[PDB]
Image (cartoon, rainbow, N blue to C red; front, top):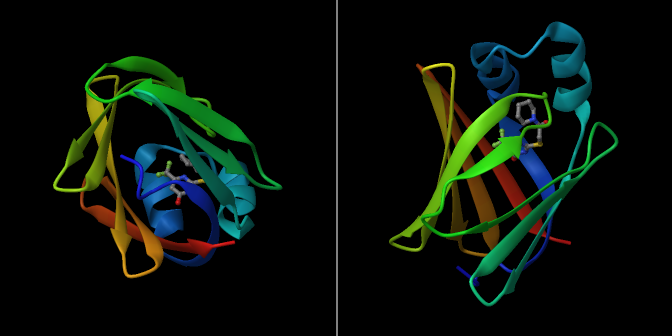
Length: 131
Ligand SMILES: O=C(CSc1nc(O)cc(C(F)(F)F)n1)N1CCCCC1
């Protein structure tokens, strides 16, 4: 992926609290995480893709190669096994932990970067625009 490269600012969020609740996130974290308006910085160097998230809540970073499972510590401190692939221009990220999973799709749509986060029956949509 590389039409994803850039700096992106959160401009809208739907159902994020519900998503965090479903994932198992404690209330105090949800309160701070849900108010935050992160920047996401995507860069690519050969086959390594780097996704940074920066906010008043927490900074995080993952670097990965498509199709290679890796250990991820999430912003809420879950230790998950993550696999990210590129599927019709959509970055498909699955996190697996304790026999559970969540799926995070990052897609380009017009000039927006759209993030869809799915946990059980909950779907949260987060839209970012170029900073
Ligand atoms: O606040 C964050 C990180 S910021 C973020 N922004 C998005 O648009 C999407 C996601 C993610 F990881 F849930 F997909 N996190 N935590 C994500 C994992 C669970 C608790 C909240």
